[PDB]
Image (spheres, rainbow, N blue to C red):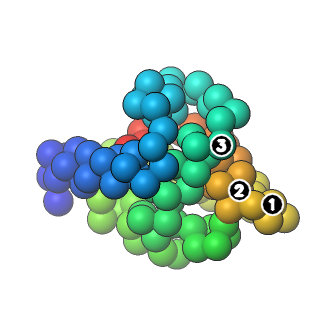
């Protein structure tokens, strides 16, 4: 429930997805600063995170599942802006067959459209 809980859940998801993908930690930190480097392992890190957050399955957005997860994990003042960005970006990755590519396109759009953007 707490923001401290969010920070804990976020650290858990980062750890697991770093371990899976073996991506540089600086690359991942850049995702919070609009540095969306075109690096396969970083795109696949993003896909890992969205799959753990129940936000995508097979590189396709599950809108209802995403909203449920956003609202559980994030405090209200961050969840609201995230929901608005998800609505704005709802169809942005449609027609992109590669899973990591689709997750990454979605992430860029969420960041572009959420002034209070955060990501594990």
Residue at the spot of label 2: 102
Q: Is residue 111 visible?
A: yes
N-terminal of the two: label 1 or label 3?
3
Residue at the spot of label 3: 40
| Residue closest to the eye, 94 or 15 | 15
Residue at the spot of label 1: 96
* Secondary structure at numbered mark 1: loop
Q: Position of residue 117 (x, y in %)?
A: 47, 38
Q: How many marks?
A: 3
What residue lies at 65% left-to-right and 55% top-to-bottom? 100
In the image, residue 71 sits, relative to residue 43, either above or below, namely: below
1 vs 3, front mark: 3
Q: In which quadrant of the rendered view does residue 26 lie?
A: top left
N-terminal of the two: label 2 or label 3?
3
Cα distance, mark 1 to mark 3? 15 Å
Q: Is residue 76 visible?
A: no
- Give yes or no for contact between labels 1 and 2 (Cβ–Cβ under 8 Å): yes
């Amino acid at each position: 429930m707490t923001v401290e809980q969010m920070m804990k859940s976020g650290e858990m998801i980062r750890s697991v997805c770093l371990g899976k993908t073996k991506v540089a930690e600086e690359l991942v930190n850049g995702l919070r600063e609009s540095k969306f480097a075109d690096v396969k392992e970083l795109k696949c890190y993003v896909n890992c995170v969205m799959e753990m957050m129940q936000t995508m399955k097979k590189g396709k957005l599950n809108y209802d599942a995403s909203v449920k997860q956003i609202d559980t994990i994030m405090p209200d003042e961050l969840a609201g802006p995230m929901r608005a960005a998800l609505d704005i970006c709802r169809t942005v990755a449609d027609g992109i067959k590669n899973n990591c590519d689709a997750a990454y396109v979605l992430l860029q759009c969420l960041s572009k459209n959420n002034p209070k953007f955060i990501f594990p």
